[PDB]
Length: 48
Length: 51
Length: 47
Image (cartoon, rainbow over all chains, first blue to last red):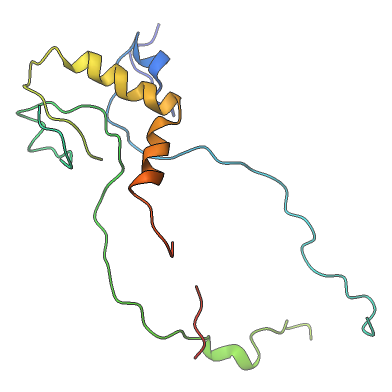
């Protein structure tokens, strides 16, 4: 149903046994995303 | 084969076929580190316009 | 990136393509980069 896949497809061993990829068009890695906390100090008491 | 630090190119790959790259490489610039500098606006930069 | 040349018809290519990608599935290639391609001082200076 589709003879080409122009989308971000991480090159993987299990994906490479059945289909053949091309030289990468972007290099990257895996990273962790978490939520930023406490954007600024309160300092409600100027006489802290 | 020819193992080593052999950068993938286009003129090369027309005549001998490479394998999957295993180290990332490009072109970059190296210069000598110099003395540290601070922003010229340091007199009022660390202060918000609301102040 | 880098690579391993071949003979343009090698037929050794597929067993090598499918072998390198297996290491990245594990962390064997990452382990080597710490052994050799590593060093100190990956800083600020008073002026």
